[PDB]
Length: 140
Ligand SMILES: Cc1n[nH]c(C)c1S(=O)(=O)N(C)C
Ligand SMILES: [Zn+2]
Image (cartoon, rainbow, N blue to C red):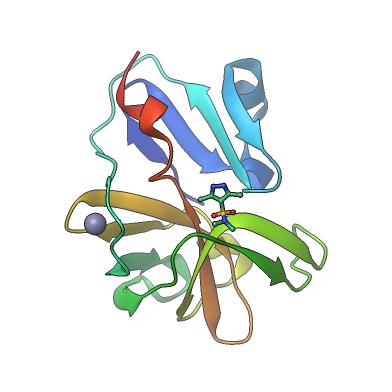
């Protein structure tokens, strides 16, 4: 599990979005595994605007933050998970690292702030859904 709390927005994995998230829906994209919903309180996280390929991610299934190198946001093919089939996914970044289904939502962060959230796992790879292209997250 895990979310980004930027201003009055909540950024979650589409596949972990709650009824409350869908009832307060701002934006959602199955191809990115992202959903954004409205909050009443302001959040404590800030979003990276950058092309960094190094950062640190939280891995719940190890209670550990790992420094990683990761690919630039891309269109990757993903093998079947407990929560999705084998399929393609967009705006995905890959690193070498541990990712189990429940690690989804872990933040990846660089020197500029939050880069994305864990979205995929398997074969000693962790995939992150990028949020850095979501400039609209900064305002309104
Ligand atoms: C960055 C971006 N904009 N539009 C798409 C599609 C993407 S992508 O990350 O999916 N791509 C580079 C493969
Ligand atoms: Zn950065």
